[PDB]
Image: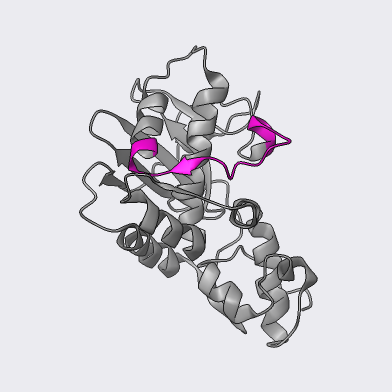
């Protein structure tokens, strides 16, 4: 009826690091590229426009030693729209405004998904990423119920998961950062350049299109990150939003 069920779910044992993060992303990447379309002058696969009720969407489950979390990636945005607690409820990014995408009406996370939520003045880039912090984050999200006291703490844990996992599907840069770092005992710590550029994927999706018709343009938006070339963009990113064919 109103619920748009995902076809299947991709379940991933996080604790057993047998497969690299490169292979993890590659597996999901191949299937989403099938859904994307080409565009002239854009090497990167281009997403479809935003359907509210598509044919399907990407449902993924990160399962650790002790805990399980499902994350809902709408294929049309490749954004983490919502989540499943193992208590059998769902959550969605927003407040006082749910969507029937998560099946039955989810709860609301109350905030967005960026550094401005957690800290504002400081960056997110100080957060260590690694096997321990992923497992901790999954535990710390799995222990949630309809009410819990450390709202901001569980929120910072899901911010590192989205930047590692979801942005990783759109960004070879954070993918390879996490690939080298996840298997480490110390983990890795990102930088301001990576932190801001990944979450503002809209800036990538305009830059890639502006580089479409003009193969040697210079884009001041993207040059700030050291990315003066579409080649440099293509080896940093993986996928780009549906950009309507305006002018480039």
Give x and y (percent) for residue 161: 46, 41
Front residue of 231/53: it is 231
Q: What residue is drawn where x is 71% and y is 68%? A: 222
Front residue of 5/86: it is 86
Q: Is residue 26 magenta?
A: no
Q: Quadrant of residue 11?
A: top left
* Residue ranking furthest to the front: 186
Front residue of 186/53: it is 186
Q: How is the image coloured?
A: one colour
Q: Quadrant of residue 204?
A: bottom right
Work out whether 1 lies above or below 187: above
230 on left or right of 140? right
Q: What residue is drawn where x is 45% and y is 34%? A: 83
Q: What residue is drawn where x is 20% and y is 54%? A: 18
- What's drawn in magenta, residue-wise? 116-133
Q: What residue is drawn where x is 37% and y is 31%? A: 136
Give x and y (percent) for residue 145: 43, 15
Give x and y (percent) for residue 66: 24, 28
Where's the N terminus, which quadrant? top left
Give x and y (percent) for residue 88: 36, 23
Q: Quadrant of residue 86?
A: top left
Q: Is residue 129 magenta?
A: yes
Is residue 119 visible to the viewer in this orientation of the structure? yes
Where's the C terminus, which quadrant? bottom right
Front residue of 151/33: it is 151
124 on left or right of 248? left
């Amino acid at each position: 009826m109103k619920r748009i069920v995902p076809k299947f779910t991709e379940i991933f044992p996080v604790e057993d690091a047998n497969y690299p993060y490169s292979a993890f992303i590659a597996s999901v990447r191949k299937d989403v590229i099938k859904h994307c379309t080409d565009h002239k002058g854009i090497f990167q696969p281009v997403l479809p426009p935003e359907k509210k009720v598509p044919e399907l969407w990407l449902y993924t489950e990160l399962k650790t030693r002790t805990s399980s979390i499902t994350l809902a990636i709408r294929m049309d945005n490749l954004y983490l729209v919502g989540f499943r607690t193992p208590g059998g409820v769902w959550w969605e990014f927003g407040k006082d405004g749910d969507t029937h995408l998560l099946g039955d009406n989810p709860r609301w996370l109350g905030f967005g998904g960026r550094y401005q939520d957690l800290i504002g003045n400081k960056g997110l880039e100080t957060v260590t990423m690694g096997r321990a912090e992923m497992t901790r984050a999954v535990n710390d999200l799995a222990k949630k119920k309809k009410m819990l006291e450390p709202q901001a703490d569980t929120k910072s844990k899901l911010v590192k998961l989205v930047v590692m996992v979801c942005e990783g599907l759109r960004f070879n840069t954070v993918s390879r950062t996490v690939d080298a770092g996840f298997n480490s005992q110390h983990g890795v710590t990102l930088t301001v350049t990576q932190g801001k550029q990944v979450q503002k994927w809209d800036r990538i999706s305009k830059a890639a299109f502006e580089w479409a018709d003009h193969p040697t343009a210079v884009i001041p938006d993207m040059q700030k990150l050291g990315i003066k070339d579409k080649n440099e963009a293509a080896r940093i990113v993986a996928l780009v939003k549906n950009q309507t064919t305006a002018a480039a």
